[PDB]
Amino acid sequence: EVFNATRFASVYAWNRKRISNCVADYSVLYNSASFSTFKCYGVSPTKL
Amino acid sequence: NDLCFTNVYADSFVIRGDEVRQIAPGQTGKIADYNYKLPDDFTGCVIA
Ligand SMILES: *[C@@H]1O[C@H](CO)[C@@H](O)[C@H](O)[C@H]1NC(C)=O
Image (cartoon, rainbow over all chains, first blue to last red):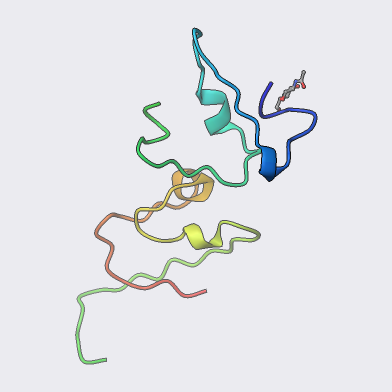
């Protein structure tokens, strides 16, 4: 619901959605080839 | 030109599109993870 959103806001008024109290499966975003770049700072993408 | 080596191997392959920069030590991505992975202490040069 955030990555496949219908319309993104302008940078002057960026949106902030809070995600909590759930099980987050991070394997779909890592294996999906639809992303042009996926560079993580702080934590490694494979241990997430 | 002055130094000497015991053996040299030339690995030749073609890559098209983006990610061409990913051919380097300690790099991540679809190409570096599934296609061609260079060692951490690689000593040599890449020409394209
Ligand atoms: C949400 O985005 C994903 C990304 O591929 C897509 O597979 C899915 O069909 C989308 N769902 C909706 C309801 O837009």
